[PDB]
Image (cartoon, rainbow, N blue to C red; front, side, top):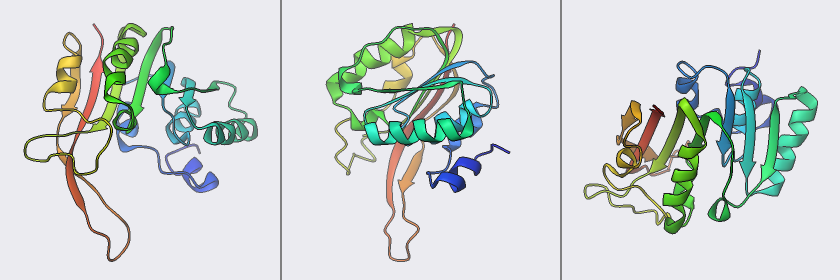
Length: 195
């Protein structure tokens, strides 16, 4: 059974993102863009559960790995591209576009146009899922991500969409090791539906 441990265990990948697992409880299978699929964990999970997925990332090796796994699992509905997100414009119509812990790694000048692109390429009634680090007065960014959302910023980006889920909750960077310190910081987490 293709659940959130299947690809994780079989192919040594980071576990399917929690927010994606939550999101498939409301977003029905449909045409999907995984913008910055990383190692493909989310793209694989989704393609294996009925979604028609376009998986894009800048890392050619990860994309080759995803292609390899695609062939073994016979996932005919998973299509990959190698792409530079800081230099990207795209056309299309998707029911679902996700971007989980990707944006903070992009140049700040990239964000406004990338988000605008995500939005015009979403079908009415479609969804966008975004998870990204923040930089706020009570938790200034201590990591030095080239980009981080300010308070209310992501919300405002999506004025006119329905906020199905939205929070700027305090999270943490943690390690599974004994002497591993935990860094608190805010993350912006949004499931938005387009009107």
